[PDB]
Amino acid sequence: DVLAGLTAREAKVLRMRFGIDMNTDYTLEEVGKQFDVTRERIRQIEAKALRKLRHPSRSEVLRSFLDD
Amino acid sequence: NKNIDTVREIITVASILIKFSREDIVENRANFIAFLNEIGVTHEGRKLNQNSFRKIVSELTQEDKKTLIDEFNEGFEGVYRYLEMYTNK
């Protein structure tokens, strides 16, 4: 927990609000796929939240031509 | 119910943002506060717009503010430095 950085409180709000169950056995590789998946779940949240933000408060966003 | 419980919630749910997906979604002022409103963490019946969002951290008891500074070293300072840097009036 200390290594990857997450507090007991943070794992609890995840399995409260975000729906992701930290409660099973966690080894290295499962922790790996779960971090991937949990992070990706936030960019799926992003999508759904930027539909509630209907009003024009957009500074800049990712089209095609200005790529990193 | 309580102000500091809600502040504790917000800092918990944001600390997550900060270390998982990082400076990408945190950046955009609207997107950040919209992530908190998505899951409906409400206070005094009100969903936290930029007034109410900063005011629960700003109008906070010095001792309970410092408690967060104290215990949540990187987590509190994380949201702190980003909110005073990004979020104006």
Image (tube, rainbow, N blue to C red):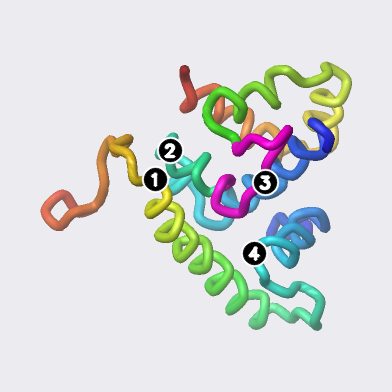
Q: Residue furthest left?
A: A65
Where on the picture, by quarter, is residue B82?
Answer: top right
**Residue B30 image label:** 2
Residue A7 placement, left or right of B52? right
Q: Quadrant of the N terminus of chain B?
A: top right
Residue B72 is situated, as x and y percent measured from the top left of the image, at 78, 39
Looking at the picture, how far across and down is residue B89, in whole percent? 47, 17
Q: Which mark is residue A18?
A: 4
Q: In the rendered structure, which segment of residues is drawn in magenta? A: B36-47
Q: Label 3's element?
A: loop
Q: Secondary structure at mark 2?
A: helix
| Residue type, numbered disc 3 | Val
Circles 3 and 1: CB distance less than 8 Å?
A: no
Which-is-in-front pick, marks 2 and 3? 3
Q: Nearer the N terminus, badge 1 or badge 4?
A: 4
Q: CA distance from mark 4 to mark 3?
A: 12 Å
Give the answer, above or below, for where B25 lies relative to A46: above
Q: Residue at x 82, y 23 (%)?
A: B66
- Please, what is the three-letter code of the amino acid marked with disc 4? Phe
Amino acid type, mark 1: Leu
**Which chain contains the residue that carries disc 3?**
B
In this rendered view, identify the residue nearer to me: B82 or B28: B28
Whole-Å distance between the Cαs marked 2 and 1?
Answer: 8 Å
Crowd band around label 3 with a 10 angstrom C-alpha radius: few (<14), some (14–19), many (20+): some
Q: Which residue is mark 1?
A: A53
Q: Position of residue A40 (x, y in %)?
A: 49, 68
Left or right relative to B10: residue B37: left
- Same chain? Circles 2 and 1: no
Q: Are marks 2 and 3 in contact (CB under 8 Å)?
A: no
